[PDB]
Amino acid sequence: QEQLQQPGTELVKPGASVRLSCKTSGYTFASYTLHWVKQTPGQGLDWIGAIYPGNGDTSYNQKFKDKATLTADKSSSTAYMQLSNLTSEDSAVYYCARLDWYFDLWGAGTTVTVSAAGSDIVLTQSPTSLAVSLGQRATISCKASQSVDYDGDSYMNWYQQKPGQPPRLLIYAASNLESGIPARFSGSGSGTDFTLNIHPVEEEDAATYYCQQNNEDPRTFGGGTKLEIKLE
Ligand SMILES: [Cl-]
Ligand SMILES: [Cl-]
Ligand SMILES: [Cl-]
Ligand SMILES: [Cl-]
Ligand code: NA
Ligand code: NA
């Protein structure tokens, strides 16, 4: 099976560098772009950059151009990201992933803990947390600052991250269920306004939900909505 394997944690000092690894297996490493993504509680997910392992070509989010360096080692099928000049602002989980919906695949993420005791499209999710009782409906809005449509298709996806699990694709192009996603999920919307619906909610559905656009570079994500079960 296709896997992207990342170390669990790195505990590091301010001002150091750290090298994160993403060991791939189960597919031809050289032939598919890999992306790196930063997650924090308050900013949700942030696209760092991408590398094509076949030739080593990279693209970076302007905001991470000085912070991140992406490389690839074809001999070990491993991609690497170095974070330089670490500060408290770099404490976060970092994932490697294939982000195009049709190739969706995520690593489990490396927690980097920086420890010293002493015109982009914006996506807004609403609500940012909610508790719903078993059997009831959850409805989550994602609104974009500009249109994410092209040729009648919406370049927006929803991701789910269940507790302790990697993120996964839930719905692609606004309204299509990814393979293996249960029918209780549905997605609607176009243009700037999108909605995820889940009904009837089950215990397995407790997770954080993120929307994402990939109409324009850089790809951007909403800040996340955490859904819990409201215990009766
Ligand atoms: Cl670049
Ligand atoms: Cl809200
Ligand atoms: Cl179902
Ligand atoms: Cl948000
Ligand atoms: Na390989
Ligand atoms: Na609102």
Image (cartoon, rainbow, N blue to C red):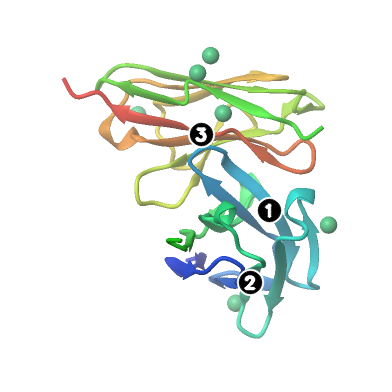
Residue 114: x and y in percent read 50, 62
Amino acid type of disc 3? Gly
Q: CA distance from mark 2 to mark 1?
A: 13 Å
Q: Check the image and name the residue furthest to the left.
A: 232
Residue 56, numbered label: none
Which secondary structure, mark 1?
strand
Q: CA distance from mark 3 to mark 1?
A: 17 Å
Task: Say whether residue 25 is left or right of residue 164.
Answer: right
Q: Quadrant of residue 193?
A: top right
Residue under pointer 2: 80
Is the CB–ligand 1 distance for label 1 below 8 Å?
A: no
Mark 1 Cα shell of 10 Å, populated few (<14), some (14-19), many (≥20):
many
Question: With respect to residue 75, does 49 lie above or below?
Answer: above
Q: Are marks 2 and 1 in contact (CB under 8 Å)?
A: no
Work out whether mark 3 precedes mark 2 in sequence or the reverse, and give the earlier one.
2
Q: For residue 224, which numbered disc appears in the image?
A: 3
Name the residue located 60 percent from the left edge and 72 percent from the top edge.
16
- Label 3 environment density (alpha carbons within 10 Å; few <14, some 14–19, many ≥20): many
- Residue pictured at 63% horizontal, 57% vertical: 36
Residue type beneath disc 1: Ile
- Name which of mark 3 and mark 1 comes first in the sequence: 1
